[PDB]
Length: 114
Length: 109
Image 1 (cartoon, one colour):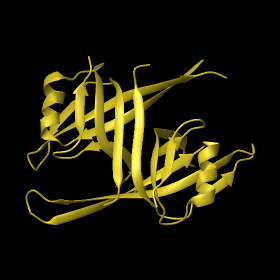
Image 2 (spheres, rainbow over the protein chains, first blue to last red):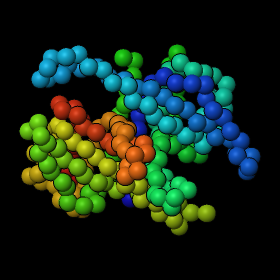
Image 3 (cartoon, each protein chain N blue to C red):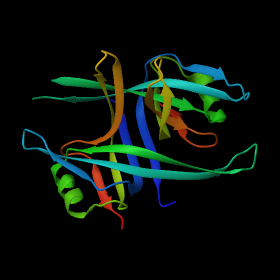
Image 4 (cartoon, chains in turn cyan, orange):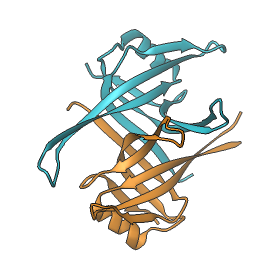
């Protein structure tokens, strides 16, 4: 292969995890995680700050059960996944893209940091 | 802080890099990088990543060395920006961003 696709986040859940059971019986967790930053603007010397929101999708059964058991709004976690951008079509036939951090079955890491 | 936003990729440029001078006078590089994964049930899936580099020392590396096909390692941060389409509707685009003075890039060929 000769490639690597790895996202590592440490952040806080913006809301309680969303756990759904797909028609197949498979569980999936969706999380929304906040990461943030501060810095001096180099030209204005103003102090700046920016929060980034990340959509996490977890298919790994072990980690779903961890999320299910332990995670709530405000929980701080470490997570490792892969970036996947899915392509879809809205009502108008227009192509749309959604980028997610995906923890596939047998992959990914989640550590509770609280 | 108590937070971290880090993406690490190794992959190949899917096109020659794009280098531009913004109105501030700063330079920016846009690259597009493929990573891939194989599996059976033999299938391949290529993931395309859109990289924006504001770090001017790393823009110079892109300019002086990188071309279509080049294999690189890059460390950056995920940023999702908002924009409006032709009909005024909100849309979103997620990019791996290397801000001024941040990020890493190593040529691997």
